[PDB]
Length: 47
Image (tube, rainbow, N blue to C red; front, side, top):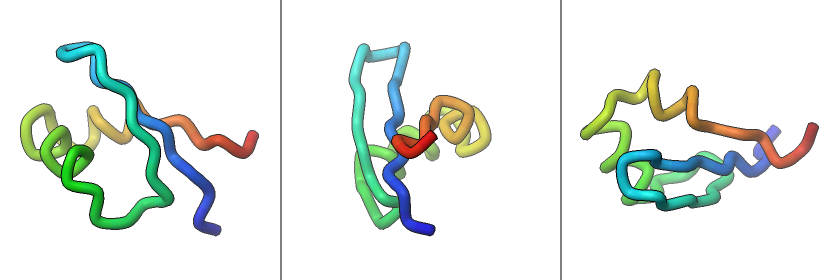
């Protein structure tokens, strides 16, 4: 429950981290490259 997901965007070089809440930069990436692709960019910081 509620572990951090790191994400990276190859189109811009950016990296971000969130617990899964309303994080505008992630929402924009899900809207602009597809949520399934962006969740494939995700990495759980607890493995």
